[PDB]
Amino acid sequence: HWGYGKHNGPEHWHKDFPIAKGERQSPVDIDTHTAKYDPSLKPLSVSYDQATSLRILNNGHSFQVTFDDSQDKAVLKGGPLDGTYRLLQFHFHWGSLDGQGSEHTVDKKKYAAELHLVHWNTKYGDVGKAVQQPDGLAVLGIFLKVGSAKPGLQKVVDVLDSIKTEGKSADFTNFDPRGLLPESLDYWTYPGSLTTPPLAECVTWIVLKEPISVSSEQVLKFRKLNFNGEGEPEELMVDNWRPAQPLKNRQIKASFK
Ligand SMILES: NS(=O)(=O)c1nnc(NC(=O)C2CCCCC2)s1
Ligand SMILES: [Zn+2]
């Protein structure tokens, strides 16, 4: 089964998921000097006030916080998007060291981690149908750098001890994902894919230009999670990031000058 190790990592994924070598794979390097400001791009609308978080879960590749997406409660609109995209879950990708961990890169710079808030287009009715559409999902990507603590992340960090290994989950209600956002909603956007299998080419990527800072203690707690399930040889959940993929016939647009 797929993972991030030598024998099951990103270089192997194409064998089970041939779209791994497709025309709109993610992540990508964002070359800031080649990205073009698109004045027709609207501001992002991040409407998270009614977000209803449900569970936090270690799925063996990351940890994710899931939300009630059965109604328009936490939605992403605007920017490059047509229509309404419901927040389903967020998760992170991170490194074994502070100089790697992000999936997208900016002028080849790797951040310590990357937060993905995964949303799906309500015109497709459910996320499984949305994954089958080229405009089915919108992932809001936010870089993490190590510096000062992010207070809105602490509640996540506080609970990771309870989901150390693959398959463990915990109640994670009343979590406000607005606490994970940077000040600026300036973004780059491009059409891409899920960065984990099945690598479906269904994502409008919206990557914020402003990172959030998290503390060394916060990221260290990410790195104490396990890829393995309980009772198996302990393999720390670190470096669960896919590297940048070929941009191919795509233009990255910037919402800002
Ligand atoms: N790293 S990422 O591009 O944000 C992602 N890679 N696979 C992702 N799968 C999902 O979100 C789903 C969750 C539930 C049902 C379908 C899909 S999200
Ligand atoms: Zn992700």
Image (spheres, rainbow, N blue to C red):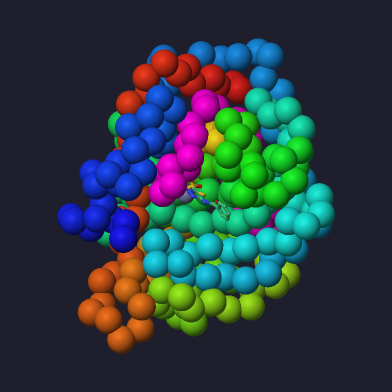
Q: Main secondary structure of the magenta part?
A: loop
Tally of numbered discs:
0
Pick the residue in front: 80 or 105. 80
Q: Is residue 93 magenta?
A: no
Residue 211 in the image: x percent, y percent? 49, 43
Pick the residue in front: 82 or 77. 82
49, above or below 17, in the image: below
Residue 121 in the image: x percent, y percent? 70, 40
Q: On the rendered structure, is 232 left or right of 42?
A: left
Q: Is residue 79 visible?
A: yes
At horizontal 41% and vertical 49% (from top left) the residue drawn is: 197
Q: On the rendered structure, is 42 left or right of 101?
A: right
Q: Is residue 75 visible?
A: no
Q: On the rendered structure, is 188 left or right of 113?
A: right
Q: Quadrant of the N terminus?
A: bottom left
At horizontal 29% and vertical 70% (from top left) the residue drawn is: 236
List the single residue furthest toward the bottom. 231
At horizontal 52% and vertical 70% (from top left) the residue drawn is: 57
At horizontal 38% and vertical 29% (from top left) the residue drawn is: 22
Q: Is residue 177 magenta?
A: yes
Pick the residue in front: 182 or 81. 81
Q: Residue 3 appears in which quarter of the rendering? A: bottom left
131, above or below 250, in the image: below
Residue 75 in the image: x percent, y percent? 74, 46
Q: Which span is picked out in magenta?
A: 176-201
